[PDB]
Length: 319
Length: 321
Image (tube, rainbow over all chains, first blue to last red):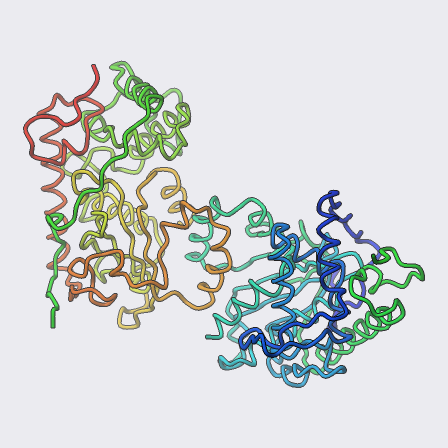
């Protein structure tokens, strides 16, 4: 039953359906239109930095930034800000600024991103993070294996994290915009061997509505006890995202899941095979996305369903 | 400099720490309190002899020591924890009585026949991984937990030890207070020689309602810290408020009531042959007083811990009868 695999799975298989989008209410539609109008302003200028935000340094949206400002981008921020228009606009604006500051505002090193595959590659050499497979709801899977840590604490560790989040996002199927994390806390002895605050700020400020599901395994009994103690007091919606003490096959198809966790995929991390495959696959996805964006006028507010798809006519025409 | 050398628990709340005032009950809360009281004052009442082996065919009346545990404040702890739902309150109190029987702590002390004795669990404390010491700003007694000082293998005795110390910190409550403060230090202590989870969870979530007044956390591993910070915005405000981290502990505890390791004035070194007998004796003396007071006031269900733990001659909370 085992399937030997050493590279990311490039497409969502036909056997996993795309879940239907939660419908907008009439009023939600009206403030969506307000966010679109704000960011479609041809004269709009936004900050060039978050940590060094200055009212004296503002620059218009580049082509690649317009491609990031999608229908679904607006919706992620609208949901995250509980549909408060000013908070939504302010949040999108500060993420645009942070993406500039951080070196990822260009949708790929091929458009000038300072954060490159070469810069962060060494961080993945022990396979502490792996993009592989899709779950029941068509979310791409990112494995985090902190016990396979291979490098000293540094800001390159943060850059590596953001790079992979950006790549797992590249892997979203048309019609899905959240990911699933699979976190294995087991220590791996076979692997030899400020940042915390920065990682926290990025995760809570600049990736709204990305966490679809977090599957936790090999939790140390003490942390587990504290998790269980706190669990009844977590809000129901956040509560539902966390999975522990359950078979991962309840949430992931067997042929999409590492065999270490009950699945059918026999995966061994081989850097010189996996890494070029990941980088190339994501690059191909970006190229397609950006080519679609240009073919549809290169405007703000296009849908990721259209940008990541191949249909000739738009599913979500703008205005 | 201003360090105070101490090696034993502090026996009394100092006069410099005020006892927080108790918020009055509404007329409706009073009526339902009276209902709980009526239920447990029933002379014919019989209760399960076990929780894990609960059986409708094995029920026994309340012993004298159990009546002494069924205080006004016990009722109130359960009423608050059950969100003032009477049936849930009565059911929960009942199952804790059963569990206390099963576990070996139904008698308010080894001196009344408890299977859980100081001797049984003493070895679990030899490295000082748990310490009862001092009182915080709201007069809560302080229990230090130092998981990095673990000195024993995983076993049911570790659970017994945990319960024993919770019961002791409860013995240390000042009259007028019934919650404790936990101070948890996650640092690894190498110089303590390197050498169930479900049971501990069940006990903490089922049989100690409304005991956690404050949890002060320190030396948290950065990864666990990150997960704590990520989940924090989604924890209900009431529980959120109980947790303190990345704050000076002197904000929550007087300096002369706090271990110097955490910014306090108390230079504490754990010395088992000094600390342990002092703890045991102090708690014992507190139990003796409480139970003597209970007997002096008729030995009935529903007496107030403020009265049982005090010395005033006349009852502040006479029982409705």
